[PDB]
Every structure is written in C-alpha cells, then in structure tokens.
Length: 194
Ligand SMILES: Nc1ncnc2c1ncn2[C@@H]1O[C@H](COP(=O)(O)OP(=O)(O)O)[C@@H](O)[C@H]1O
Ligand SMILES: [Mg+2]
Image (tube, rainbow, N blue to C red; front, top):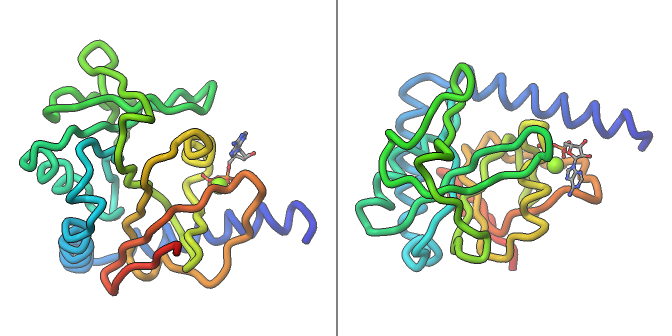
C-alpha cells in the first residue's frame, strides 16, 4: 500500500497488456476489431450521438479508423484530440476528412489547428475513451499521461471504451484522480455502470 507499490503495479500492468496487444496476430486484430465495432454501432448512445469524440488508433489497439468512416457516413460530427503536453489538456477538434490530420511524431496523428475547429466538451455527445486496461467497474489504466483523467473531470456527456477482452483485469490500483468510464465493449459483450 506504499506509493511505489501503486505506481509500480500500474507500470507492470501497462507493460504486460501492451506486450500482449503487440503480440496479437493480424487475424486476431482484424477479426476482434471488426466484432467490437459491430457491437458499438448497435449501442443506443452511438445511434443517438450527433457528435462523437474519438482517438486515432495505433499499432494493435482496437481499430478506430472504420469508426470515423461510419460516423461520417451517418452524418455524425467527428472530433479528435490535439494534446498539449505542457498543460496536459486536450483540444477536441472536428475532422471531416483524414487530410486534416498531421503526424506530430513517428506514429501519432493529430488535427491540424489551422485546418480544424475546436469543439466544446458540452457539444460532444459521446466520448470513445482509449486505454490500456480496465475492470468490470469501469476503472481504467491509460498510457501514463493522465490526459483523460484530467479531461473527464469537466466532461459530462456519455463515455465508453472499446477493448479486447484480454484488456480486462481483475484489479487496478486506482488513485483519487483516476476517472472511470460508463461502458466497456469487448468482443464478448459489455460491462456497464448501472
Ligand atoms: N485531474 C488531475 N489533475 C492533476 N493531475 C492529474 C489528474 N489526473 C491525473 N493526473 C496525473 O497524471 C499522471 C498520470 O496519471 P496516471 O493515472 O498515472 O496515468 P493514466 O491515467 O494515463 O494511466 C499522474 O502523475 C497524475 O498525478
Ligand atoms: Mg489514470
């Protein structure tokens, strides 16, 4: 229960799940990503959202590119974050096409400020929240920046996360600032806060 025990457990779990994700075959990535998103589009909060906030997936993370395409097809407004590393804040900005993105390093894609419009949190109906590991309780370990933990303080709309079932864990050592998500969709079903 010492502070280091907590931080070391988070790094340990983050490391272990990332390693597992990276080991996923191409077949598993493709099939599981397909299943998870098919289940997303059946959700009431998808159908009803007129503006959706989402991240651009990397490596073997559940594939969000098809989700953005579907949202565009359905006439939904799509917003993606630009992170400010100094303030640890996110500016969700609308994208109508993938040419409004730039690579802000190696594999990390963000909306080009000059070509995109910031959208206020109170205008975003659903936030699809990225992450590394989760519990049945909606608890969440991300990548270590604490961006969503900070953002979710002021965001009052609906939240959900997409996850492979192996990203589900029994216990996460949550700190007072860790924010939970309302729903998790895996290839096996959904975990909901009631
Ligand atoms: N609401 C907040 N206000 C201030 N600092 C925060 C807040 N939320 C998270 N942090 C900080 O962000 C850092 C990373 O958060 P952490 O929970 O460890 O990562 P993650 O949520 O990405 O898995 C921690 O050092 C923590 O102090
Ligand atoms: Mg956290």
